[PDB]
Image (cartoon, rainbow, N blue to C red):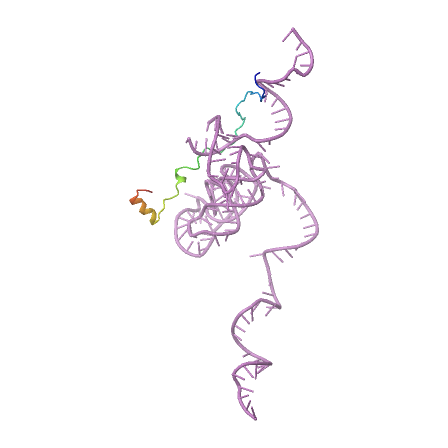
Length: 56
RNA sequence: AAUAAAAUAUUACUUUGGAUAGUUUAGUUUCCUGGGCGAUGAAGAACGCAAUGAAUUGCGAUAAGUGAUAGGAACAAUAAAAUGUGAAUAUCCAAAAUUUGAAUGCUUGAAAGUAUACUAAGGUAUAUAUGAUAUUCAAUAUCCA
């Protein structure tokens, strides 16, 4: 057979097909635009940057 | 020989101290009933959440609370808003339940992360051992054309 090493023969490999759902969690993303941003920083340091550097 | 400044003694008042007396939402022991946790993710740990919170209590991105069912007019340190079209308060109920932890895709030091598949971001499944069934294979191991 021109080689010595014996390996495990490859067989058929079906994909996972569960008979019932594994989770029933609601498909709602809890990290949206309204949750990512809490509030702007209102310190005197953060106000100076908004004018000269045009940064929020 | 003399002095009463210091010293000593008694009592009253005050002071430092916290004994004594009065008291108990705390313990100790015995007895009765149960002895009801977890891969449907437990016990434990960590982080976060109150209009003003540091601890503690309760809770989990629906946060000192949501729905439902009872319940009947409060809470308060200070404001506010809501409230008999239902405030407090109660629960073996419903939804929801962050990071971990047997911890279970791989890694984990105080480590930030990251692979594939299914349904960019999100969410699920994939550790080890094991029983049944299905399917694909390996070995002339026994026959065997």
